[PDB]
Amino acid sequence: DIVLTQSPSSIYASLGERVTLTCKASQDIHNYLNWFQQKPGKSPKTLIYRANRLVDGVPSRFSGGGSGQDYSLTISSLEFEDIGIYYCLQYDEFPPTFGGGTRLEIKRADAAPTVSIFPPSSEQLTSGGASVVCFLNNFYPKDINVKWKIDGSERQNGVLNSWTDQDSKDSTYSMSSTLTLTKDEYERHNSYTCEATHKTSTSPIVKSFNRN
Amino acid sequence: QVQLQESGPELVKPGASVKISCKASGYSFSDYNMSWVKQSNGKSLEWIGIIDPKYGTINYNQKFKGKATLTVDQASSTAYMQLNSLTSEDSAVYYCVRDYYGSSYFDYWGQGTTLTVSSAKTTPPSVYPLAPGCTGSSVTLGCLVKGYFPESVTVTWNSGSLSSSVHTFPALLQSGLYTMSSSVTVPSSTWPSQTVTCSVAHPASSTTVDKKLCR
Amino acid sequence: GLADALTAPLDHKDKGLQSLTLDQSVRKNEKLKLAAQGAEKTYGNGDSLNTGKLKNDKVSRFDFIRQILITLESGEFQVYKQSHSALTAFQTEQIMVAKRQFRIGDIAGEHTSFDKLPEGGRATYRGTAFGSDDAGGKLTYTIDFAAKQGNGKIEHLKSPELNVDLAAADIKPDGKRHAVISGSVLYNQAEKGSYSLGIFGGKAQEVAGSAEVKTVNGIRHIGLAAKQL
């Protein structure tokens, strides 16, 4: 089967910027290439066929190019409705095969996270569990480190982390980090700390509570 | 009314079979091919196979032979894909896609059908309030929605009247069960002087839980 | 004959089309080794193929090896020659492991300028349609120069889905203002692909180009060339 590769895997760009996405096939695919755009929770939408033909009604800011193995899709002037993931596909030799996708996201000014830490609720404890939750909200860029410390020592184990997609309104990211413990383990210690390191500051943001 | 309207989401056990439909309207169904595409984890896409509704000819991606069977019913303008011997690796979103241009196969897409194959049992969430304990101009509050299945859950804050400052985090799957948290931020002038409530609907277990954020 | 095509220099006295520039047929960093009748020559993106030595109105076959030197694919290279146009195609056979695909290479010749077409009259062209393992197709094509429209049909191919109509389409200028007709391919009256023909010769004596027919197994290429009789 022909292999299709897309680079880079993520692109950050500003509104109005020129953006170029690339696709490479493992052999000459004779211009039989589609580009699709997909928004979160939505179906793909075809933008290009035969490498350089615009689907009817697609804005003229889009164009496809390339030949042999090397193709690109260029957006001449990025608009907000263009944000999403772009996939290429070859249909020169069946089975048709897709590239891995390039996500196009919006650049914005760096923003420090708002960090909040929450103790287990009495309702969870009464059932023998103890989740400690830290929200790290509205930050940019997406790269972030969260460390958990219990009685001042780094908690190694039992961390689940979840990230939102880029926010439609302010272009930031948010993340939750959950330390889950048995009720007995939780009651073994006093102090619980969520600490976030992010490029917006040399000093970690630290939020704690003390069980006493 | 949309051209390619697929059948609804499916939740089945390993070993089962499902048949997904793709009803065509607004164009000449028999004159255009219909393909099917699998998208795993909202990312990786694969082409399964294609059928010409007029002539009945089919081509399958070798990887899907013996997994998928394509058919059509020309009279009702419907294409079908049956997936047999289901395992959790078949959980995905499936799309039908028709062609339109003379030199393209993949031009307009159905809305997608979500298939979940699992042996997990329907299980209501435990909902736990997340309040600071043990403060500033703005206070962030939360609700932890833990240990539910299947995945469809909806969290609202003050009966949905608070939404602009809400973050809902993607669920994570653990012991066969999902866990998700939601956060909301309100002015310090609001909480704790006033009750803020999160409501959690998990329709598969007939759950609509309300939890107050207090103290 | 084939060997002379590969070894001889051009001969102003040979029947045109005398030369064909290999562009699509051999990409930037490829070498294309053609062999026939004991001879071999290597090209050469940009290089000229001595079609003057080949017979008009027939497909000439060479063994080919495409390389980048390491071998990518091999099979049979096909050239169809008219007086003012010619085209090439590749029947891949091996890539070693058996694997077949048929794809058009270059369509070349003395393109008729869109700005210097006949001002009127109806021309009929008759020639060959050739695809994988089959050079016996017949192309009939008609151009009305008053309407600047063309239409035609492909018949007599062994594969039934390749016997298609080439539906009516306007002549338009391409990026060099060469006259070209790009249109729809019909199978049992319904669209199943696309075609493109250029018009060639100072008096629009010829057409050459290709059709692409969608099947459930992929797109099949048909090379096309016809001339006024």
Image (cartoon, coloured by chain):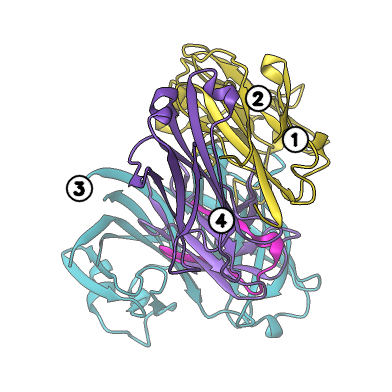
Chain colours: A purple, B yellow, C cyan
Q: Residue C228, percent across and down?
A: 61, 68
Residue B175 is one of the magenta-drawn residues = no
Residue C29 relative to residue A59: left or right: left
Residue picked out by circle 4: A86
> Which of the image's four quarters has the N terminus of chain B?
top right
Q: Residue B70, percent across and down?
A: 57, 24
Q: Distance between the residues labelled 4 and 3?
A: 35 Å
Q: Distance between the residues labelled 1 and 3?
A: 62 Å
* Mark 2 element type: loop
Label 4 with label 2: CB-CB less than 8 Å: no
* Placement of C21 over or under B75, stated as above or below: below
Q: Which mark is residue B9?
A: 2
Graded by Cα atoms within 10 Å as few (under 14), some (14 to 19) or many (20 or more), the crowding at tag 1 reads many
Graded by Cα atoms within 10 Å as few (under 14), some (14 to 19) or many (20 or more), the crowding at tag 2 reads few
Earlier along the polypeptide chain: callout 2 or callout 1? 2
Amino acid type, callout 2: Pro
Q: Distance between the residues labelled 4 and 2?
A: 25 Å
